[PDB]
Image (cartoon, protein in one colour):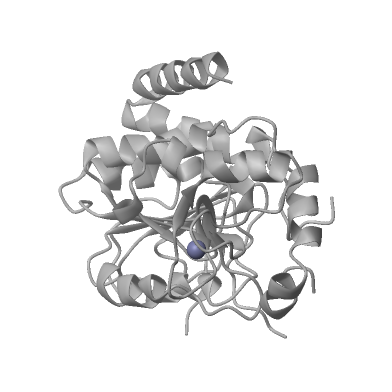
Length: 279
Ligand SMILES: [Zn+2]
């Protein structure tokens, strides 16, 4: 298809973003954008999460949650860059594979977000006739005092709104995909190796002309020899660009090219201070 980037660089993406053509940005994000906040990637080595088992034995999962509880919920530069996109009126949607709620704390609203694997921000009574919603504050303590969270109305198990193995993907994902990718002018992929399906396939739902920027420590999204993946390096490459390093440093570099660096700096400092104060 046609070429909208004058150059396959971050500078070329920055100019396209500043041009009249780029109105609607979609962000595809994973564990990589949350590693610098102190949230470990579950897909990295650096049954318990099966739904049938959890309802029978919830203690192991809540014990693991009690242990791997992060200590402080502070969103990174990459999270506040997406809040800047929203402020500038460029954010169509953020598709996240994370469950750490850092997107919402950075100031992305529920309608801005497609949480492909759910979120800890909200919890629900597992009883269909009740489904009493409990916040993260209520859940924290219940995990803290090692007192299994039970519904105050019906005494059923209270589960955080994350998608365990065996659970179906949020219908929101498929419905939003069908609508969002008819409109997207830029695909901003950050902190994901694009190995988990069907999230990885979202990149092929971009129109042929839609530029796609990967900000990651290593390259990813390329078609596996073992329809159309990421093509950065080949002679046919026309729209796909890769920036290699910390997601935070990459977003900071893009913001710098866009003239947002001070606004981003001031936002991250202001919000980090606010969180530090009440934590
Ligand atoms: Zn209930």
